[PDB]
Amino acid sequence: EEDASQLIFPKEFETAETLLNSEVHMLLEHRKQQNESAEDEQELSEVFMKTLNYTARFSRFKNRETIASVRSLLLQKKLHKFELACLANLCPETAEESKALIPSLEGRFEDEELQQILDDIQTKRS
Amino acid sequence: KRITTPYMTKYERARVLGTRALQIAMCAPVMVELEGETDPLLIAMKELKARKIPIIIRRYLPDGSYEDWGVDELIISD
Amino acid sequence: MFYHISLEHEILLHPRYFGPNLLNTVKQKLFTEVEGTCTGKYGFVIAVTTIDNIGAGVIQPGRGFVLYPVKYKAIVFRPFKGEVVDAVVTQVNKVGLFTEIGPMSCFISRHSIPSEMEFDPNSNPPCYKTMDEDIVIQQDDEIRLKIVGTRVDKNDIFAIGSLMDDYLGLV
Amino acid sequence: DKVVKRPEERVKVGMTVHCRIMKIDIEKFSADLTCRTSDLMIAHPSFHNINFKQAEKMMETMDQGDVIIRPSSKGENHLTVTWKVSDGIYQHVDVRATLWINSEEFEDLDEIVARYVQPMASFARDLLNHKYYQDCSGGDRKKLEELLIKTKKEKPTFIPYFICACKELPGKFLLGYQPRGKPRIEYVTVTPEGFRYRGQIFPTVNGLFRWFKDHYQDPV
Amino acid sequence: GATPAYGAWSPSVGSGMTPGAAGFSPSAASD
């Protein structure tokens, strides 16, 4: 029954806080910067290393202000939290591609209304 | 706004001494200079006399509320 | 998908650790207790960002161990079905394609792959191309996919991908 | 060993002895294994890679200001800093004198002393050159009291003062005076930044004296 | 250990009464 396509999740996960690829990347980078210092400390694990190199290959933008601006311009809409991560991460070129990838957008908003947002996101990309 | 008695009941004193003795016997740091004794119960008694036991008692009331007292806060009976 | 939620956990602390660094030791144990693990309820946890507070350690009766119900603000990664993500292809085999969704690895079958993407066993690097050889897909490529199934192998998530929907390849 | 007892210490009889192999004679039933172990192959901060009783034997030679860092003898990952205070008086700062510090300082120990011992050492030495200074065999409580009553008689009008440092509790100076025919004692602590007299902390050493010479007139 | 904390002791101040007159020496300049 758990299918993100139809916007259904467990109660505990419903109240979660979405994260973006750049957001998690900078969080992990700062954690690594803090941990590397303060000698006599248990070093990072392969999980941390793999997650770091996995998120580093999809950092659409390095500027925390870029992250802030995109989330601020996005939250003003009526879309659910789940729509804030996938759409902000994939950065599709056209509204048709976005609608095809995410079935939720089908009929939820106008074509130009979504296309302008997609163009804004692409532009915001560094 | 604590209304429980400001004296340590014999029950609480006994239990505190016992628990501190067990902790010491489990190689825990002491809170008083040792004059050359080894018995954990004796060390616990000395700490109780010196009012340095790092333990706080939580007295529950019939209603459901509770009050946290520090061993170094309330008066010791014996 | 990565998320930032507040979790709770309790740890017993052996009395040998009592001292001026009690809180520090509790934090260290929490770090090296709830990092990298996985659970079927909240999913796979990456790391811990910060700690909310330290509860009141309740010394057990007749035992020196004292438990601290600490609540920590950490992040978690619990992919769900139907979500679309961008992974990197790790290996190409006639049996299937192997990718790496961060802390998780999926796998797609040739049946999921359309008929247009044939095999290239003759070429040294295992790769799939079309008749016109215009589009090329190989390893170390940011290829997208859709999570159509999930699985937890005793705290080891291993989902399954798919390549049927259009617009799944090079951006 | 050739014409003497067979080599027993060099080669383990019955057991296996480790030695450097300098010959490959497996096929020839030879083993050129060497039985010998060799075959197989002012402000002078010192260091110490020691106990407490034996350490005191090497503290009375250095002059004032020579600081020495040694391990601790209470727990683990602890250090004790000892700086020369006076003749026989030594403060053993047991760093967990609960001096709270971080862990990054462990890598470089060239600033802990220069930040909390050097100024404190200078302040302590400032009192050593004081005009009215004495030791009285380590400054014992039984010997420092008779001096006040023996010195008041020669000058009942003028009430002089003295300063000394105790031996059983290093780092606590005794500043006594005789308001009347009854002795009184007042301790004082020397903090890293300065002193701690009546709860106040002064920036300079002379500040304590200047503030003390204007507050002992009260009846108390 | 045989070397407990020495700087952690709280210096207790002694109390008393001495109704004396003001006839002691003056102060000095801090320079």
Image (cartoon, coloured by chain):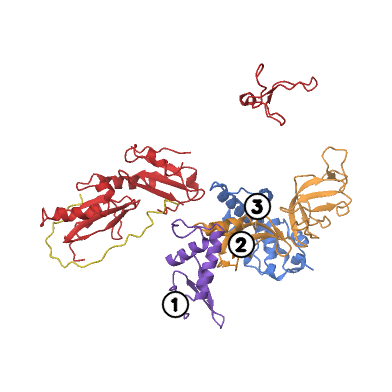
Tag 1's secondary structure?
loop
What is the display colour for chain D?
red
Q: Residue at x 42, y 43 (%)?
A: D53
> Amino acid under label 1?
Pro
Tag 3's secondary structure?
loop
* Number of on-image labels: 3
Q: Is residue E17 above or below residue D102?
A: below
What is the display colour for chain A?
blue
What is the display colour for chain C?
orange
Q: Chain letter for purple?
A: B
Please provide percent x and percent y for residue D7. 66, 23
Q: Residue at x 26, y 50 (%)?
A: D164
What is the display colour for chain E?
yellow
Answer left or right for D178 relative to D23.
Answer: left
Chain at tag 1: B
Chain at tag 3: A
Residue pointed to by mark 1: B6
Tag 2's secondary structure?
strand
